[PDB]
Image (cartoon, rainbow, N blue to C red):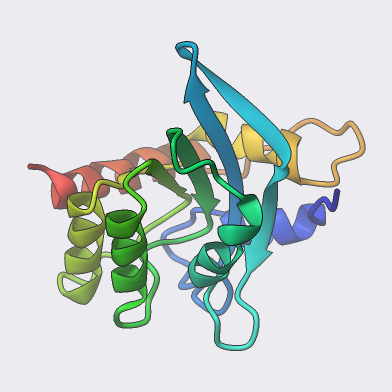
Length: 182
């Protein structure tokens, strides 16, 4: 099971708002079955994806859903830890929205390291994700450290936060919440 290089993680998940990092998107994913009150994980149902040749990571996750062989009779929670949202292209959120409409046994939780508020398409795309049932939030220390511990080739090294991580996360979270306020 393949683990990310540590500089790739740090370079892509850094939440400095003064950086406009839109070239790549890294999406770390885990799928759990909701049963017996608890959650049940599957290690072959965890991994990470980047954009590959114009096909956004979010779309690459949707392409591998069949290979997950989800029992349509059960409820599943898919979590994404994604370096930024929402997916920039037009209708790429629409493809996510559509997948959620056709797979009503799947609940999608999106934890983004950052968002880019353009006061336009970006806000509308985030709202449409919410409206299709996704739960979108901004990553905090706990989630960066989880992803470090879970997806990165860290060789026993502990997570080392960058300067401003918590301040930046709280500022982004405030703005996402404002956008998504019902």
